Length: 54
Length: 58
Image (cartoon, rainbow over all chains, first blue to last red; front, side, top):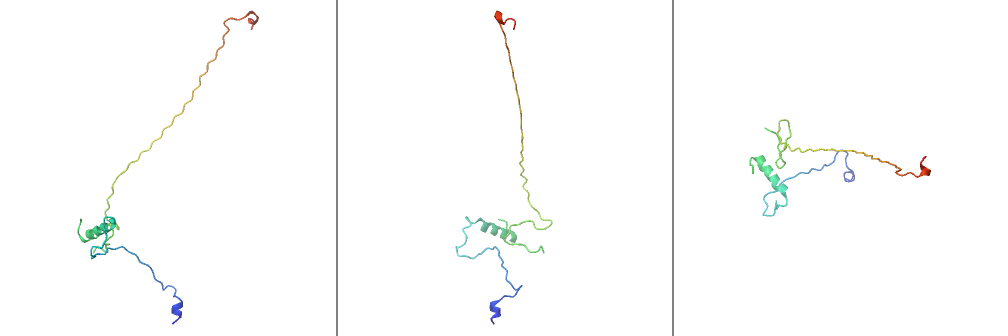
């Protein structure tokens, strides 16, 4: 059980994924949204997608 | 079904038939000008009002 600990197999590799999201349900410890316009912009985007146009 | 739609991404046109708003704001202004000039004035004179005798022949 040492070769598996010393080498890696060609083609058997890991990639990296990134994305943007919103986290809700905080107890008043979220963004101020006055210094972060993108939070409100993306919340409005989500609401518009769901059918609400602010 | 209209396919996958991102939740937080800004609404952009992605496929054929999608609409987009163009704000036409064009302001173009070009100009050019040039000139050239040249001048030349020349005056010359010589007169012998009173000629002494020894200079008369000349």
